[PDB]
Image: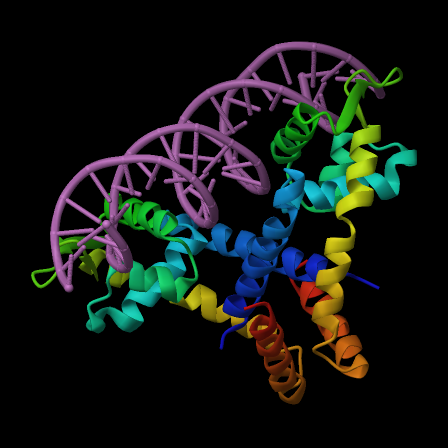
Length: 137
Length: 138
DNA sequence: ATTTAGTTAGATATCTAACTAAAT
DNA sequence: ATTTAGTTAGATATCTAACTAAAT
């Protein structure tokens, strides 16, 4: 089996399983992780470009994702007072409640995954993944 | 220190991007490349649209759209089976075959520059563990 | 004059639900 | 009456290119 096949499938399947679980929250996988990131780093408090950089997503992409979240009233955006170009992002109380609500799912997946592999194997695995991801700049 | 989902997502994304970049000169996408590849390797079996759906782990509509794209590209031909006309058969065109023969080198070159760093033992171990994980999610 | 942050437009990949055509 | 094999419709995610607006 080629590597591309492997990764593209374990990630297609991961995305699918995640969406299946998140169906009761009316958000997608990507929105779930974005919401989570915002949960972690809200206090910073980051612009859209920061999210783009942190997530490996282009500007228009995150613009659409964020406009989606904002339509679901899970986040809020305002213009920075110092740099009118910038758009500062924050979680609303609904967004925060939601993040506190699904987050168990992601952890469930991570656990159900690591339970397949012995800790030495899991550690060597993550190390080799990190190295591979490093290879592609 | 990194969630598995993060690593897999990111890796798949960078692979898809580099692939798309190198494939731009052929005016196809990563997915089209792999589809044409699968056609190349299993054309002989009379691949129905849904057999491709099963093999690529994509859904019927998805496959329909990608195939329709490739057909618009004239890289593939479509016809209706004689034994069962609710089903239609898929085939590589000569343009398509030449294309596959042309770009396969990219997927190989990438798979290569990826495998090389990891020692062949670590490589075997990794493809094995990866297979185990994908097995689990399936 | 350039550089940077965000939005728009056009175009693929992908999913589920609904639908048409046709084997059983 | 019931399944299968593709298509259509409507949706989200993503990227490139061209855009407006705003900072050097």
